[PDB]
Amino acid sequence: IPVIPGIEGAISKSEIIALIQTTTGLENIWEQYAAYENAPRIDPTGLSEEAAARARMLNMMRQAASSRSILVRAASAIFIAQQQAGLPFETVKQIIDRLNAEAKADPDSTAGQVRRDYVEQTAAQQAAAWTARNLEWATYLAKVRGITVAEVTAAYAANAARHGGYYQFE
């Protein structure tokens, strides 16, 4: 594992994300776990105390490599960094909670850029799912609107991104 300079004096979730980014030199702070893409989960129950902790750490890497949520991925990676650097233990829910706040306080920070990318991603998944549920409805809309079917999916995603991830009628 690469060493994180002063990971122990980081005061905010945004500053932690930015530290991992500069020291690994990777687009997003979870690319380093790519080997664990689609790894089977591990049942830690019954194992020795030591084995159980190692399995929880491996299962957290599987989450950072696999989760369908950018917010889960970012928080998992931050979890792993805090554990390796012996930072005070906080759960993945606490991490997400703290960076949900730091993004509302300043949407331009690293937390905020992360939330924006999570909303945009959720909006795209919502759009694809809706499309695949109402294939004929999307096609009817493309015909009438004089556009392609994918351009219709894109309009849904534009709408959903404007309202925190989910479609709402304007």
Image (cartoon, rainbow, N blue to C red):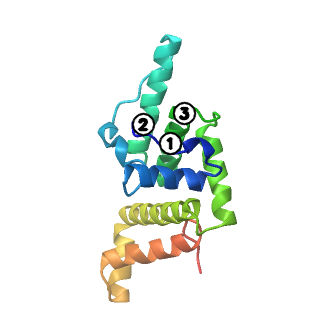
Q: Which mark is residue 135?
A: none
* Marks 2 and 3, the one that precedes in the sequence: 2
Q: Residue furthest front?
A: 5
Query: Which element carries disc 2, helix, strand or loop?
Result: helix
* Marks 1 and 2, the one that precedes in the sequence: 2
| Proximity of marks 1 and 3: CB atoms separated by less than 8 Å | no
Query: Which element carries disc 1, helix, strand or loop?
Result: helix
Q: Which mark is residue 61?
A: 2
| Proximity of marks 1 and 2: CB atoms separated by less than 8 Å | yes
Amino acid type at mark 2: Met
Residue 77: x, y in percent? 48, 43
Q: Nearer the viewer, mark 1 or mark 3?
A: 3
Assess disc 3: are there few (<14), some (14-19) or many (≥20) residues with their C-alpha within 10 Å of its C-alpha: some
Q: CA distance from mark 1 to mark 2?
A: 7 Å
- Residue at the (58%, 69%) spot, across then down: 108
Q: What residue sits right under mark 1 in the picture?
A: 76
* Marks 1 and 3, the one that precedes in the sequence: 1
- Residue at the (41%, 60%) spot, across then down: 129
Q: Is residue 70 left or right of residue 100?
A: left
- Residue at the (59%, 81%) spot, across then down: 170
Q: Is residue 170 above or below residue 163?
A: below
Q: Nearer the viewer, residue 16 or 113?
A: 16
Q: What residue sits right under mark 3 in the picture?
A: 83
Residue 33: x, y in percent? 36, 41
Q: Nearer the viewer, residue 40 or 86?
A: 86
